[PDB]
Image 1 (cartoon, rainbow over the protein chains, first blue to last red):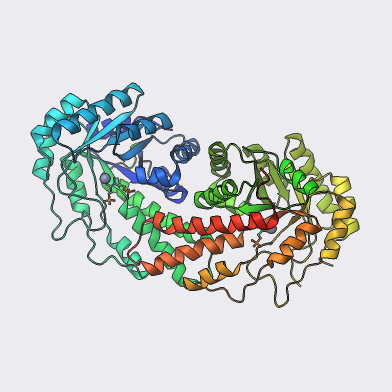
Image 2 (cartoon, helix red, strand yellow):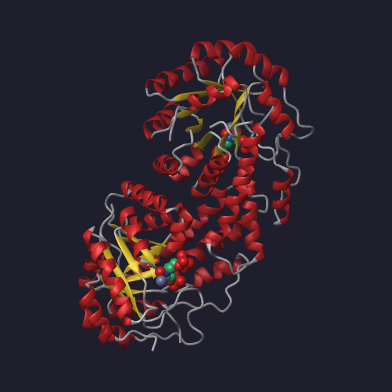
Length: 294
Length: 297
Ligand SMILES: O=C(COP(=O)(O)O)N(O)CCCOP(=O)(O)O
Ligand SMILES: O=C(COP(=O)(O)O)N(O)CCCOP(=O)(O)O
Ligand SMILES: [Zn+2]
Ligand SMILES: [Zn+2]
């Protein structure tokens, strides 16, 4: 049952735990996420990038989530627009039924980012939808004092502080390093739920399965489980996870393709994929402490 | 927009053309099928096996179709339960929103098959839902349909359409040698029943699809489907609904295997399924024009 993204993140902010924000592009991904939340009794933060919406059609994105909500009525679910690049996009998501929208204007200067974000807040809050913004650059780092004013004047529901992460299986070209001292300053000055982008970990088991199936993850490096927990302690309440889901999913697809070359039954390809993806999500929920929160 | 399967097939039956019945198991397959019907201006017959419903959940199966119907309000769409094995199964489909159901009891004796079909018919017809039944066993080369038996069966059950066994079968391996269908037996059934007929296991395994699968490192172990000529012979023989599934799977997975081989560092699902959809869409588009359902909307 769709609920405001803030309704989920304010609880996580109070009690000091993190809720996983998992991306999806189709049915297989969506199904495995809900089943994971059901078996872990965990809140669900379902994300959809603009590239994913384009792929599915915003009508199918919301439509499929609504259907899933009906079969799992006891689970709190927030539908979040991931990385909206324009006011129009966020507005379309709001009209479509999204309960949470992100307006990514980190590339802009402070004033521009603030004005565009404020405009989005006015619109979304009017329709009862939560809003997410971003300061810093996913590649530089966030200015705690900027975050303080930014949050105060925009009245945004949650903020994504750049502390050293980035999307993809290749986050660190060296030793994984995040600015936790900066994260804590931001948390103290804003006192709102914080979001961590590019937070995939690339677990040993997930990497292993992918490489066994003839996949190439040479040099890949995500955020260690240690750091993910330090982030939550630091004030991170929303943890974006996508790469991990993809890798674990394709790992089984590649495997099936190798084992049996006469196999063309989609269900035989995506059944193991869903399972492998569900397990990654289940483990992540327990890691962040969102398990048994319902 | 959902329409009773009979609405689509009755037009095909009286105009003498065939409508493709395409199976789906998820969003990708469904989307490619709709875009095919849209680009070919063809009526859509969408069906799901009990295995597909198990995989998706009958709520999602129906839910996804209704969403697609909304983004394509000008295309007649029939939601069909493929190979329902029980009354309860057919009853669930009816309640879920299906517009057409098949009750497959062809493995039973005439009397049992008739008894079950009739019970399903009375229920489905009460909810404004069409029904399909089957006489004869879907096997390759009595197993073929008895024309007289079909006459009484249809006349007594009042079933909407009938799937007569004339030689086809499911899978990529239908013919071990020369393809052969009993078109004489088909025409007698059509004459005696005078209703829309359905052809099961009617995948052709086109050469471009076969080649594509083999290229991506796939293995078609002496697979052979129904030649394009046979399918056209079937339609001229009285066939109005043509079950297609294998062709879709193969064309789809072919593109999946390809991407896996081409780029081993690729793990973006959209990069795998975008080409897979396209390949599937083109298969459906060609089949629509072959069967002659193109431009009927
Ligand atoms: O934070 C992340 C990614 O985190 P991860 O790579 O560590 O999983 N995200 O918000 C995912 C953004 C989705 O992008 P796209 O669908 O266009 O490729
Ligand atoms: O006629 C056919 C298939 O014909 P084809 O194999 O020639 O494409 N069908 O009704 C499809 C039956 C679906 O079976 P499953 O349980 O594997 O989902
Ligand atoms: Zn991100
Ligand atoms: Zn069949």
